[PDB]
Amino acid sequence: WTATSGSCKGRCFELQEVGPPDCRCDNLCKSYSSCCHDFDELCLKTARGWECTKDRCGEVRNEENACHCSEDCLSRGDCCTNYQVVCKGESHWVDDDCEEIKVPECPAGFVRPPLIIFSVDGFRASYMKKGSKVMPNIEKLRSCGTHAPYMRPVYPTKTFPNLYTLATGLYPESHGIVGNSMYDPVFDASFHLRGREKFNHRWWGGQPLWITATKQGVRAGTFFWSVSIPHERRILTILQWLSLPDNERPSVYAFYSEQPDFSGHKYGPFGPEMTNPLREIDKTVGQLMDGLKQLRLHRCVNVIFVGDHGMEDVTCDRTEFLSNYLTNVDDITLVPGTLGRIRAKSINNSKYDPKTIIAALTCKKPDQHFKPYMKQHLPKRLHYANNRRIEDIHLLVDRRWHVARKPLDVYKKCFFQGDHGFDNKVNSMQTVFVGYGPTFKYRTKVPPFENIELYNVMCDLLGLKPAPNNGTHGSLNHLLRTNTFRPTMPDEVSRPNYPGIMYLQSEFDLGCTCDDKVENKLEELNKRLHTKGSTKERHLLYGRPAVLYRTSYDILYHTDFESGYSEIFLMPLWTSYTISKQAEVSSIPEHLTNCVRPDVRVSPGFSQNCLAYKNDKQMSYGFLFPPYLSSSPEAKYDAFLVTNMVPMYPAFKRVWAYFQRVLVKKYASERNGVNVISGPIFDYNYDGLRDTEDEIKQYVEGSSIPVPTHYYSIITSCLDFTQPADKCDGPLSVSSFILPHRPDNDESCNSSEDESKWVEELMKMHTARVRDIEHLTGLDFYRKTSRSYSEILTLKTYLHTYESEI
Ligand SMILES: *[C@@H]1O[C@H](CO)[C@@H](O[C@@H]2O[C@H](CO)[C@@H](O[C@@H]3O[C@H](CO[C@H]4O[C@H](CO)[C@@H](O)[C@H](O[C@H]5O[C@H](CO)[C@@H](O)[C@H](O)[C@@H]5O[C@H]5O[C@H](CO)[C@@H](O)[C@H](O)[C@@H]5O)[C@@H]4O)[C@@H](O)[C@H](O[C@H]4O[C@H](CO)[C@@H](O)[C@H](O)[C@@H]4O[C@H]4O[C@H](CO)[C@@H](O)[C@H](O)[C@@H]4O)[C@@H]3O)[C@H](O)[C@H]2NC(C)=O)[C@H](O)[C@H]1NC(C)=O
Ligand SMILES: CNC(=O)CN1Cc2ccccc2C[C@H](NC(=O)CCc2ccc(Cl)cc2Cl)C1=O
Ligand SMILES: [Ca+2]
Ligand code: NA
Ligand code: NA
Ligand SMILES: [Zn+2]
């Protein structure tokens, strides 16, 4: 119940929300059908429209008008945004030359530059260039401020997950808004685009920017706008709030536009109908900037122009139907569209089986336009698994396509031509970032970055301490003129042991064999130097990774590679080696095919054994440092040490051997040498974070050798490829991957073919940031470079996407 008989007199767009049944006058009362009876008359005035005209100038104030052109309107803070232009001979902001804002220029009583977030739904990144001729105000923000060529949204590339990511810095699996539609099995409740469940605070986790601000004594405008409040009124309300007295005035504000998404869905991303909504957004920016100029705030306020996701061409004829795959289609519930999520239709149906569903959806039709995954097998870069609202079975849908359950869903719910939601590396999903203001840099282009980084920067812009989030604070300091956040590198928690030769060959009973008993003061001192680390500077180029948790491990040196060997997990946490452009690939010699060699530095009790592999019929082994890239026949024996061995399913060894035998050398060729750090990942609870020992669900049969869920590699070179990776004076270049360690190659439908036709494609799908690897391993990389620390943070957040040009 709302007793709508109260009044909005002097309450229009009030910032405090009054509680039921008292009637509301805030910018959301419409969405709750709770506004006071006179809210439209008083708060949504439209008379005479939104623009001053010559004959209105100096008019007698008429309080009924939507906005004013009377002499008192500046002091009342309610002029039409074009008032000084029409009536006082001023220029529109867009018409003024851009001039650097070196310091804030704020009216007295302003304690800090306010922040205004101008949020545009479905604003595809390439609109900034492709629509530039019809967006002069936005083009001026972009060219005169700080801009990225695109900003990467989070997956799924849907509105609710992305806006709530922008406000919290959190992945949707963490904040809990994992789609536009959701079922929470603990609540037994459904969240929908339409209806009243979505306003229940229990859905929304983390701490959004307006809560962070309020807790720290920084007042906030309301961030949400009812769809029926016209955009001109939204702008006027913000400008009115900015004329509040100092003690009452917010420091952070948000505007929202439902366009261009609304039209993009109807017309496609580049339909001829799309020019007009771009013109209209630009005009609204122009209103804001003109309004700020009138208040003498246009060189005081920081403005962020930001989108949530892009828009792709999708039509209802490009829909895949589960009813062409599944016998039991009526036994499942599908969340459909540009992603699929499947769960049992009834929890009382004991004939539901996710394995038979996955199998029936796997590589069934030659051109099939979606791929099924258990959520733990999705690319780790999507960070889309650790939430009970994310169904176990996921369909990744190809760009331009939909998935639906049955054809009747699509015609008896087709006119739509655009949609979004796909993989967040897809070019059509990328969106926009521009920042303009005293705190942002001047005429500066920054590389693309992820929207999970923005909350930290928004906190910086406002002097707030951010709540714990998934950004890497400092990774965007290069966007900022001032207020940068200068972090210190985390302290190493575990120091390594440096074991020398401690065990005789006969102390080992590992069941391994090697034909190496084939036999010099020249060469012997040399090989002792290698075991003491004399080649370490060439293979460990950026310092040893720091271990940020408590464990026991050994540094092992070799001619060709250095490793940090875990006594707890019986294998390296990391293996680091450098391959120059001149390196030669060689075979594993016939007599060495099955060679594994005890490591006389490491006790038998902390070693793997070969018998466990012989006896585990499902599990084989591979090596982290590749025997194919040994520097000499003699150095090659080091690659067969038991301390360089890792457990690998035979199907996985196909991928790994092709990476090591072919792809490493290709990258060294293309990049002028590469440094590679490889290792295992254990993430059996799919939380994106390093497992402890007691979370490991699988061991090599009969043994304490834990099976990795993934293997990573970090592949670093000189950004200026005219210098070789090992003599790089400047910024670095990196690509990394986190490959799932799976017992089949069912993910790759072309896997019966030669590895040259599918392996690299798999690796590209599983591209990752170095930061993703850090979370998964508790290691901290790039500890010793000549680069600034924030530069390194940027490098660690880089994702190599392999998409063509935006
Ligand atoms: C991205 O950034 C985020 C933010 O930094 C990272 O997320 C954090 O990760 C931490 C570790 O996983 C985690 O810390 C835990 O906090 C628990 C207390 O939980 C509440 O309090 C916090 C703080 O206010 C709050 O934010 C939480 O919010 C979660 O849950 C609510 C309601 O369910 C949601 O609305 C909200 O969206 C959020 O859900 C997300 O996180 C939870 C995990 O908490 C997931 O379950 C969800 O699916 C979703 O992703 C909570 O309201 C605390 O209880 C934990 O402590 C346990 O473990 C430690 C080990 O150190 C130990 O001290 C205790 O023994 C304890 O164990 C006991 O409970 C076990 C489980 O029942 C049981 O098995 C044992 O036997 C014990 O009884 C833990 O310290 C922190 O909560 C989140 N924060 C957020 C916002 O997500 C994220 O990791 C980053 N991602 C990457 C990849 O880097
Ligand atoms: C009832 N009416 C609406 O909700 C309209 N609406 C759309 C919407 C839909 C789902 C989730 C959030 C929002 C928020 C959107 N506001 C904005 O984007 C302005 C900036 C902003 C605000 C909030 C958040 Cl969480 C993040 C950001 Cl960057 C807004 O007002
Ligand atoms: Ca884990
Ligand atoms: Na085996
Ligand atoms: Na296959
Ligand atoms: Zn949309």
Image (spheres, rainbow, N blue to C red):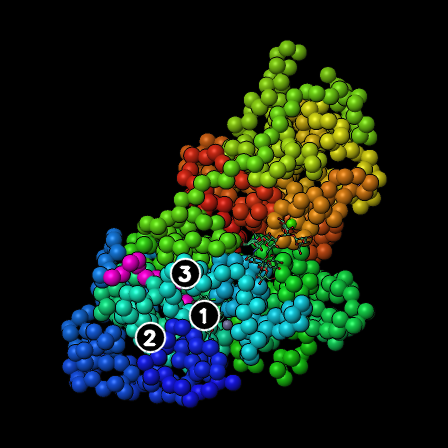
Task: Kindly tell me whether residue 174 is visible in this rendering.
Answer: yes
Image coords of residue 615 (percent x, y): 84, 40
Image coords of residue 508 (percent x, y): 79, 25
Asked where in the image residue 401 lies, by quadrant, the reply is: bottom right
Dot 1 surroundings within 10 Å: few (below 14), some, or many (20 or more)? many
What is the span of residues highlighted in magenta in the rendered image? 109-126
Dot 3 surroundings within 10 Å: few (below 14), some, or many (20 or more)? many
Q: Name the residue under label 2.
A: 237
Q: Label 1's element? A: loop
Return the mark for residue 213. 3
Image coords of residue 205 (percent x, y): 54, 63
Query: What is the C-alpha distance between the residues marked 1 and 2?
Result: 20 Å
Left or right of 187: which side holds 275? left
Can you say whether 143 is above or below 772 in the image? below
Query: What is the C-alpha distance between the residues marked 2 and 3?
Result: 20 Å
Can you say whether 314 is above or below 35 in the image? above
Left or right of 155: which side holds 348? right
Marks 1, 3: nearer the viewer: 3
Q: Does the residue labelled 3 lie within 8 Å of ligand 2?
A: no
- Judge by depth and name the residue closer to the eye, 751 or 79: 79
Marks 2, 3: nearer the viewer: 3
Q: Is residue 113 magenta?
A: yes
Q: Name the residue under label 1.
A: 121
